[PDB]
Image (cartoon, rainbow, N blue to C red):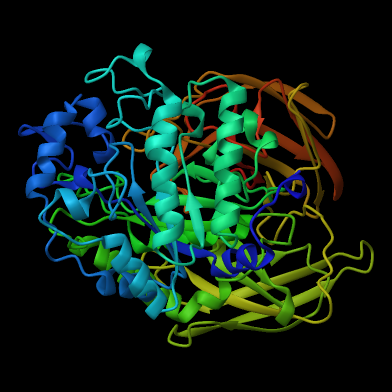
Length: 586
């Protein structure tokens, strides 16, 4: 029902689609030399942004930190150059977070970095100016619902240490601080690619009041920044159908199921365990992991935002300069396989990586994230002739050979790529560009591969009914026998303590006239190339007998599987990566 609202301009949405990959910046007073996850010399296990709320810092005391906040080495050109180095095409910056501190010159409010600190500079102005000079699209985040500085801004996370939530008049916060500050953002910094919001569901006012205010907010944004993309976290999921917005937001860090969503969305990741600068955080993610997550999101049809920060001196931490420089060196070679590409059209995933699509030039990009088993990639859904394959990176030593065989009995084309190379997937993934002849022609088949394996995943599923808890795949066996059946499911729970929560759960398999109950056990752990740090857990369910070649149907039942949407914390649904049939000693 997006067509029922004004919406972003066509040219604004097309700019966002082409851009693909962006930077997020969380930076504020919470990055102070004496804060950044510490308070009064004590470490708190909390993201920096939430330390004022977790440690209940009286605002009279919190505001005193502004008096010696001077990030004197801040350099907007250094920040935008690092975004461009990384191969990012847009940046979104926190103008005001939950702490209520404006990281820009706010005429309406004195609690702002230009007026209240010895910095005496507007970093949002400097970044917007640098972005204009370097043709990088520039957007802003504003914490519209949560504000711990304003005595009226009551929410589900109230400042109940300085103020009494019962005495709040939310409309006064809204008229006196929220709307004047949003107007400043819409007027002071030129054309905005994005206006970004979160915690829309933390509004404790009546639904009708929320809907009226968000409607008015959105109308103001379309009027003053008609080309700006807005995310649905501006509200709660149950009010999305009532309100204007352009795109959704995926989980923080946790990878969406392999499923093409019927809406536009960004995935979003941290570069470490925190958002804004956290003094003790030495858990910097690898370039390899974040490239794999970028490619995995674009294979699903999403945009992707990677968050960075700056320390209290206004320096980008060296580990994040190194990280984005390493991503950049990869993007310089491989960006055409990621930026402005479409989601996989193959109607199946693969254990070895993911696929993106450039239909205008008849290209499929195979993102090889781990060594394919025996150096072979098997396709059965591609009907087109392959004109050629090439490594995008001409410094990789070796060659990709391929065969295509059209089986005259089934009409199925078996395409087999043979990787003759010696690449270290631990350092970075590699891209094979496959050019196909004619308009892309795919048949949604699930087929046993060269190594006698069948992958059943969230993309190639035939039928699912979350009410009846039934999940069905139909697939072709070319090599009969007795094969092991494994469920590969994900860890969940918080990124600093990932856990697999499904021990002892019972369900059923039915296939090829065989039917039995299994009990899930943690049989094996493995890295999941698209997730950090959540791992794959393998549970051996049992054995299926395929006495001859032909078509079989397998039904998983009596246990819920997350197919088209997943939860990070709730434990009723099992987050499916895939079910595998294969050689019982592989």
